[PDB]
Image 1 (tube, rainbow, N blue to C red):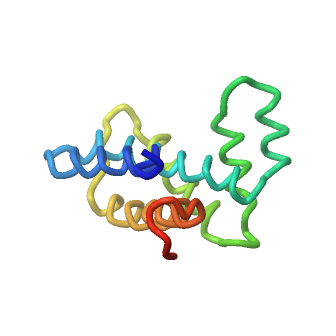
Image 2 (spheres, rainbow, N blue to C red; image 1 turned 30 degrees about the horizontal axis):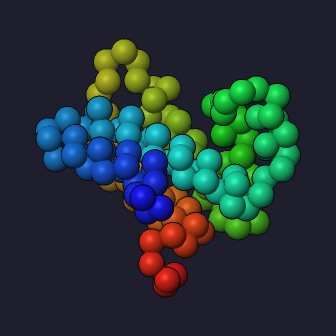
Length: 129
C-alpha cells in the first residue's frame, strides 16, 4: 500500500522476466524502476529547478529526468552515471535487442542502489534505515 512503490513493482516485474528467460524485456522494467527512483528522489531531495522545468509540461520528460540525475552529485556522485548507463541500454538497442547479462549484472546493481536509496529516503517500509 504505502510500500511496494512503482520502483519496487517494476523491479519485481524485471525479476519475473529475468527468471522467465528473457533478459531484454526485463531491462525495460529495470530502466523504469530506476526512472521511478529518480522521480522519488527529485521530490525527496527537493529539486525545485527540476520541478520548475517539468511544471512547464503536464508530465515528466526524459531530459528532465536526465537533468535531475545530472545534479545530486553533492549526495551521490554515481547518480548521473548510473542513469546514463540505464539510458544507454535503451538507446543502443539498435533494433536487434541483444542485451546481455554481462551488462545487466552491472545495471541491476546500479539500479539496486537507486531503488534501495529512494525507498530508504521515503522510509515507508519499516521503522529502520
